[PDB]
Amino acid sequence: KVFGITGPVSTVGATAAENKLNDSLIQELKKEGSFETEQETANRVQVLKILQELAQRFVYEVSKKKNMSDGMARDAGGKIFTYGSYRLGVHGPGSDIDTLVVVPKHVTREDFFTVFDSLLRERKELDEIAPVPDAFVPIIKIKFSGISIALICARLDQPQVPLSLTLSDKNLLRNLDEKDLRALNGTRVTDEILELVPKPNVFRIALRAIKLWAQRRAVYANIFGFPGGVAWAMLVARICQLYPNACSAVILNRFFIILSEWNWPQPVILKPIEDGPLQVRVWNPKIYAQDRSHRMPVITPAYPSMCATHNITESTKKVILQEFVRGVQITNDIFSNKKSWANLFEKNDFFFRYKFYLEITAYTRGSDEQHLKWSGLVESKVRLLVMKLEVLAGIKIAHPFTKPFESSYCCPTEDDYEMIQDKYGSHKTETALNALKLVTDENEEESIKDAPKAYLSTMYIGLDFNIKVDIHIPCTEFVNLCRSFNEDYGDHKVFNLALRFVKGYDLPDEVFDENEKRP
RNA sequence: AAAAA
Ligand SMILES: Nc1ncnc2c1ncn2[C@@H]1O[C@H](COP(=O)(O)OP(=O)(O)OP(=O)(O)O)[C@@H](O)[C@H]1O
Ligand SMILES: [Mg+2]
């Protein structure tokens, strides 16, 4: 049993004391809501039934539009595969379902963003929709029967996709567009990770703990330059390979030690990187300057191997490492009977730890869908601002928080919209925004539900200075950069973007939870 | 072609 590219660090098995801490770890995971209910799971499976119905109808309808016979259009098939954390079996109650739609050659992504998009919109169950056709991997994001779904589409080079099709055959990848290869590899990567760990259930528990920890410590969000689900999965998988007989609790301790001691940017790799024909691009820092720039590379096992942490910046690297060091101290303390699992999973203090914050607000006076598009675009560029800021001589760190803050306002007139852009983002002025603000208290209320809305999504970057530092160049670049995608958001009567420098004590109330109090 | 699954 060779798992991975080296032998194990240790084949020593778990002691009674370690197994006791493993039992306690699992109980803390349960208490903290790591595992969804049976009903919640049933709800996911029901969505998957509908998505398959839609996928096949999608392929049939496209086929017919391309003048194929009734019988041939049916034979074209189409199917779905899960991928991501639900397929891996480490999802929680709040996790999305990642769904890959596999379609034959005559069905393209333009079809996906027109016909399949159309089919989703017919559904009474559709709560939200935000198509993102221009992304490294194009996606339709939806909320369906209250469940977040991520939908991507891979076009195979064959006339038919039978329901029985599997993705094991590497021949299926021949000559495929880069975007489709990435799509198919969502599913293939999950399956290979499970193949590459000595004890899948030890791996699953350890990963559930790392997902909870990373969420709590605010080091989980691919979009903002932190590792996402697959990067965290592969990191845990590597530790599992190195300690094949350890319990999950011990894997956590070793995870923090090994990854804090790791000689970054040496890559984390789960299996020898497969060579392909010269037509196919594989992660290789010797050939590609871009790959050489990856700060903490975590490489997917599925051919062709890619880096799952391209978005990591100098600042987010420093934060991840700080958190690993904390993990070492706390897990050691847990194993020496001084601390609890609860201590490890304690919430971050992002909004207490810096003197200064840069506040980024995307405004939309329009539909919820328009706001999802605009705010999604802006959110996707925040890491670019982080990178521009962190290279400025006077900046010690530019630390992005991992989730936007959403709010909406009743906004009957053009003048009201201009007022909202004035008063928001400062605790000094934020009380004046009410009572236009929508709350879970009065949202049911006919006047509130019926009113035109202005929507806000606000992101924060924590700032620490090497010292006033002039930050106008990165900020102005960012403002202008977002505007040009392309002319879709140039209308200032509907879309706006504002950046605000804010000191810690003037941070909005939204930022602090019930248990917490303003500095 | 500034890597939103
Ligand atoms: N940056 C990336 N590099 C490589 N593959 C990725 C990347 N981001 C997403 N994926 C693929 O898409 C899948 C789903 O992405 P998603 O962001 O939903 O993460 P996940 O693993 O499902 O975890 P969770 O949804 O619980 O946060 C991943 O598991 C992975 O296979
Ligand atoms: Mg997911």
Image (tube, grey):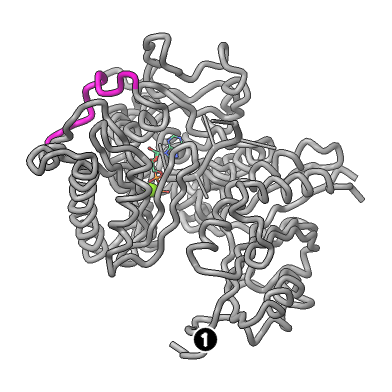
Q: Quadrant of ligand 1?
A: top left
Q: Which residues are magenta?
A: A163-175
Q: Is residue A163 visible?
A: no
Identify which residue, A170 or A39, lies in the foreground: A170
Q: Residue furthest left?
A: A71
Q: Main secondary structure of the magenta part?
A: loop
Q: Residue furthest bottom?
A: A446
The answer to whether residue A171 is magenta is: yes
- Identify which residue is drawn at 89% across, 47% down: A469
- Identify which residue is drawn at 38% across, 11% down: A275
Q: Is residue A281 left or right of residue A423?
A: left
Instruction: Give percent across and percent down for residue A430.
Output: 72, 77
Q: State the image quarter where residue A160 is shown.
A: top left
Q: Is residue A47 left or right of residue A164?
A: right
Q: Residue furthest top?
A: A278
Cβ of mark 1 under 8 A from ligand 1? no
Instruction: Give percent across and percent down for residue A339.
Output: 52, 54
- Identify which residue is drawn at 23% across, 39% down: A66
- Compared with A301, A517 (above or below) is below
Q: Which residue is mark 1?
A: A448
Q: Is residue A318 left or right of residue A22?
A: right
- Identify which residue is drawn at 28% across, 64% down: A122
Q: Which quadrant is the N terminus of chain A positioned in?
A: top left
Instruction: Give percent across and percent down for residue A405.
Output: 59, 64
- Compared with A513, A355 (above or below) is above
Q: Which quadrant is the C terminus of chain A positioned in?
A: bottom right
